[PDB]
Amino acid sequence: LKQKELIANVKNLTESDERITACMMYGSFTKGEGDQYSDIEFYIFLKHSITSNFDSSNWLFDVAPYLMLYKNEYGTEVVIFDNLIRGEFHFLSEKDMNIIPSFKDSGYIPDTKAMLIYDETGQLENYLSEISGARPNRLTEENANFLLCNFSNLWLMGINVLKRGEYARSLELLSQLQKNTLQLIRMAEKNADNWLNMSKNLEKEISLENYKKFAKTTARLDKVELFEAYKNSLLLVMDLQSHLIEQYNLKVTHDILERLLNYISE
Amino acid sequence: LKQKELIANVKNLTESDERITACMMYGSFTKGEGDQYSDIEFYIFLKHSITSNFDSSNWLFDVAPYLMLYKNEYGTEVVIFDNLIRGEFHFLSEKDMNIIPSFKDSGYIPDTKAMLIYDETGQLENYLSEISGARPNRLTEENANFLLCNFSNLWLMGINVLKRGEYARSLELLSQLQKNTLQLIRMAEKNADNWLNMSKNLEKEISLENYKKFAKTTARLDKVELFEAYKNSLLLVMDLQSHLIEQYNLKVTHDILERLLNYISE
Ligand SMILES: Nc1ncnc2c1ncn2[C@@H]1O[C@H](COP(=O)(O)CP(=O)(O)OP(=O)(O)O)[C@@H](O)[C@H]1O
Ligand SMILES: Nc1ncnc2c1ncn2[C@@H]1O[C@H](COP(=O)(O)CP(=O)(O)OP(=O)(O)O)[C@@H](O)[C@H]1O
Ligand SMILES: CCC[C@@H]1C[C@@H](C(=O)N[C@@H]([C@H]2O[C@H](SC)[C@H](O)[C@@H](O)[C@H]2O)[C@H](C)Cl)N(C)C1
Ligand SMILES: CCC[C@@H]1C[C@@H](C(=O)N[C@@H]([C@H]2O[C@H](SC)[C@H](O)[C@@H](O)[C@H]2O)[C@H](C)Cl)N(C)C1
Ligand SMILES: [Mg+2]
Ligand SMILES: [Mg+2]
Ligand SMILES: [Mg+2]
Ligand SMILES: [Mg+2]
Ligand SMILES: [Mg+2]
Image 1 (cartoon, rainbow over the protein chains, first blue to last red):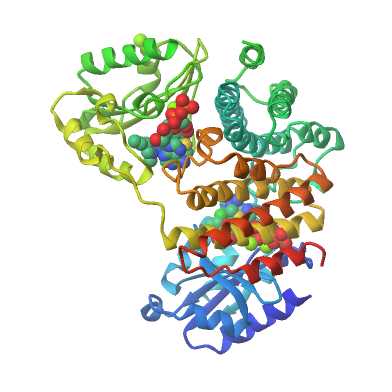
Image 2: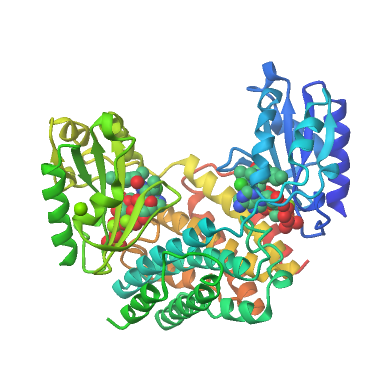
């Protein structure tokens, strides 16, 4: 894989460069899920007093020639290399390595070994041993209530804009509804490790039954298709709620979902 | 309108309640766009001493009985009243009233008069006057570049996950692409006030030609429809880039977009 050649380059350069004190890899190549379709991604920890003006544009070209480079909404440098591999490099002071513990909340981190690329001081390895084995419990009453409330809110907003004739906006809301629904399916089927990344591995991780029901909640930009998708979204959540009620005390009841259902033809 | 009755109750209670110093309304009922499909929304500014313990659930019930209340991801109290009207209420200390001037970054502020629901001290009116008539100018090289780079980033990521067979994830990414594409159309057509709310009034605000093109970038959860939508997504952005390049210096060139296009079948 071209990706692995680039990863090796990153390891090489982060070790040899005096400006870089640590490098943490994350993503699929640290979880046995890397393939030819994957990107590569790192936190690059820099000498504190040279962090502001660090020439990351030049450093990234030293990794490999690139076609495009910009800073995304998360402050991460994103590169499209000339071989079309995407790379995400988050550059920050070594003094901000204390961000790492909060990563335990992002998902299941069974192993940390592939994450350790370079570690000048030993501090990176120490932070990683704090998150190694991290596994958020997603199967909570709190989560079930938030998702059902969040869905009801978004569904009602969506059906309203649809009734107005704001079709494109109802489609946008439907995609937000869909993310929430995936999280509900993962709750109902007790396979919720891929939580924030709810669509990762979906074809491998959920029942055909609910996959097909989810597919029915999708639509192109079309009034009739949107109405069908919105209706099927509600029906699916009604199924999920009647399953989840057995496990949690829910504030969104079948009655409340029934009122939303009736509203479609109002 | 049920909405107007509820706004009236909010006006009534915010005035009379000694714990509430000011109430600012926003959204479509302050922008000449309110209708039967609208929600209602307010910032409620509380006397500083009681902000910490204020029982919002109790107060919102006084506005009208509700079927559902929860805090969304923005910390907004979101309510579905028992007549199925949606309400969004942001409770803050009076001392945070100075967040108001930053609202000018969100878009055009046509009517600060309709925004003033209650103002004990005259303070709210003063902050609102600072934003009246204001709008960002979205027509910039910085915006053209970010959107084209962000689109290219998300598109290449999305086509990779589609090729992988992660269809549900490619759909999720497609919806993110779609929002970037609406902002790009708004730049090209120079109708960019509805920027963060890019799909608001979309059917009324962009040309029939670009609406039709945008509609072809949409898909249901289906391999063939997804490949069609991803191609049409890039082709639309290629059209838009050819216009934008005349106005701004752009990092994303036609040649780069063509590399991405050829990548679909590689
Ligand atoms: N919404 C989210 N919030 C927080 N962390 C997330 C997240 N989505 C993904 N992540 C984390 O960031 C890592 C990198 O994510 P991405 O590169 O977007 C997908 P990936 O799992 O690396 O697969 P891929 O790049 O091979 O397609 C993921 O493995 C996950 O640990
Ligand atoms: N993404 C965003 N970021 C920041 N502000 C936004 C935003 N989207 C919308 N807004 C602002 O928040 C106001 C209320 O938004 P919404 O209630 O979601 C839509 P609306 O314009 O009120 O129409 P509607 O409620 O009648 O359908 C908008 O009018 C706009 O001023
Ligand atoms: C052990 C996981 C480390 C991850 C590092 C950190 C992070 O930088 N995530 C990014 C996150 O952003 C998107 S997915 C929304 C990218 O596709 C992904 O590769 C990653 O860079 C955002 C801030 Cl969520 N995440 C919170 C967890
Ligand atoms: C005069 C506009 C005032 C608005 C008030 C403030 C706000 O609370 N916006 C909300 C925003 O959130 C979503 S749309 C993302 C809601 O649909 C919308 O009614 C509004 O409540 C988020 C924090 Cl962006 N926005 C930054 C601007
Ligand atoms: Mg990755
Ligand atoms: Mg990534
Ligand atoms: Mg509104
Ligand atoms: Mg609203
Ligand atoms: Mg009461």
